[PDB]
Image 1 (cartoon, rainbow, N blue to C red):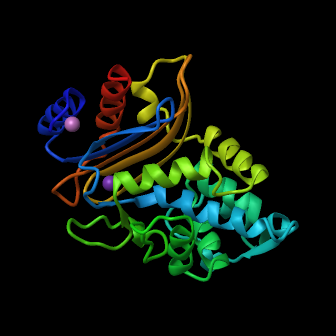
Image 2: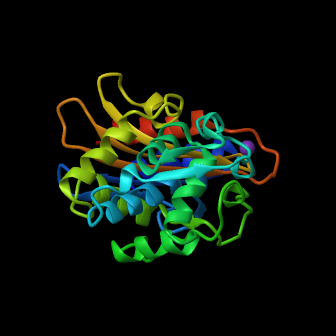
Length: 263
Ligand SMILES: [K+]
Ligand SMILES: [Ru+3]
């Protein structure tokens, strides 16, 4: 079948010139709306949620872990380091690195999370441990954002990512304390107002993580507390044919608007 919402999402996609992937979980009824839900997309920095959550899981058996100093060296800086560059030749804790990675999309911070997990494969191992058989992290930042069409590296499907983000933020993949910390971090994101947020009514609350990369790749994954409604989890992933394509955060906003109007 093609549902009315799917038909609208297809029309949006047709007019964007790229490829759109959407997955909604409505926790009012534990149902799912999917558009290219089983196709792979490059995650770009949306993968930082999985890395931060894996460190939060480690902290369940190490109560001081998030206060653990990590040295930041000049060689650690990469292409986008708004927080970490201030701490070169000093230290940041794993809490600080998690907050920087999630709320500012600091790539040096993400790389410290990855290193704490033993490399990209450690992030994938955490995904598997929480029931996500689809996610894969293969590279550090920034090369995880190359977003080359057809490349399986650093990809997931909308279905899998929605289901993971539910489990992490609303379910029991993390302990109580850790889940609340993750939600606090996502709600404090600085980078999201033009993406899913921009398609929703003002009164709805959002916590999200954006991503972008080559091929005009423009992504957002969110938990949403609508006015008067049980929470939603929404993944919107968008990528384009030309390497140098311009971000399209408006397409994500439009997808979110269609989903909101279809509840
Ligand atoms: K880009
Ligand atoms: Ru159907």
